[PDB]
């Protein structure tokens, strides 16, 4: 129940592109984890997966609370914590994670509304910290250049 202070600057386009350039590279990430559409702009931070304008729509219906959707080419006002969620997840990660439990469900309003799915989301939040906390904003990867102030 901690509101959370605000003493840091949001990630710029470049930085955001750097976090997506690494995830996109992957063949299982550059394809809508749902159908497999290549260059899946749409991305779901909740499950840190890649979706396509087609599928992404379904998620939006569920409710930003159930599955938040954010583009990569347009949406630039991303949150450090979020961005990571994508790196600390991946498509395959879920493709298996789910089965491991035994979802045996395809439906979007069900497969995602199932326990197996939930477990994932939470997990993403945790890991996201490992990367986020790391040198706070300073892109763990390397020193991009801290702006005076
Ligand atoms: Zn799709």
Image (spheres, rainbow, N blue to C red):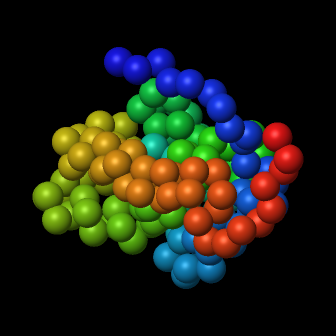
How far from the left and from the top, in percent, is residue 134? Answer: 50, 58
32 or 129: nearer the eye? 129
How far from the left and from the top, in percent, is residue 141? Answer: 61, 71
Decide: is 94 above or below 111.
below
Decide: is 11 above or below 38.
above
Q: Residue furthest right?
A: 148
Q: Residue at x 39, y 71 (%)?
A: 92
Q: Residue at x 55, y 46 (%)?
A: 82
Q: Quick one: quadrant of the N terminus? A: top left
Q: Would residue 37 be seen by someone viewing this image from the given angle?
A: no
Side (left or right) of 129 relative to 99: right
Q: Residue at x 42, y 32 (%)?
A: 66
98 or 132: nearer the eye? 132
Q: Residue at x 52, y 29 (%)?
A: 64
How far from the left and from the top, in percent, is residue 32? Answer: 55, 64
Q: Quick one: quadrant of the C terminus? A: top right
Q: Would residue 7 be seen by someone viewing this image from the given angle?
A: yes
How far from the left and from the top, in percent, is residue 38? Answer: 64, 72
Side (left or right) of 95 relative to 102: right
């Amino acid at each position: 129940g901690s509101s959370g202070s605000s003493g840091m600057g949001d990630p710029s386009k470049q930085d955001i592109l750097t976090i997506f350039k690494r995830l996109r590279s992957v063949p299982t990430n550059k394809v809508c984890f749902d159908c497999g559409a290549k260059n899946p702009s749409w991305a779901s931070i909740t499950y840190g997966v890649f979706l396509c304008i087609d599928c992404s729509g379904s998620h939006r219906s569920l409710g930003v609370h159930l599955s938040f959707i954010r583009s990569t080419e347009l949406d630039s006002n991303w949150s450090w914590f979020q961005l990571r969620c994508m790196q600390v997840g991946g498509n395959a990660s879920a493709s298996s994670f789910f089965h491991q439990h035994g979802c045996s469900t395809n439906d979007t309003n069900a497969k995602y509304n199932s326990r197996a799915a939930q477990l994932y989301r939470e997990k993403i939040k945790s890991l996201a910290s490992q990367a986020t906390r790391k040198h706070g904003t300073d892109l763990w990867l390397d020193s991009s250049g801290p702006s005076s102030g």
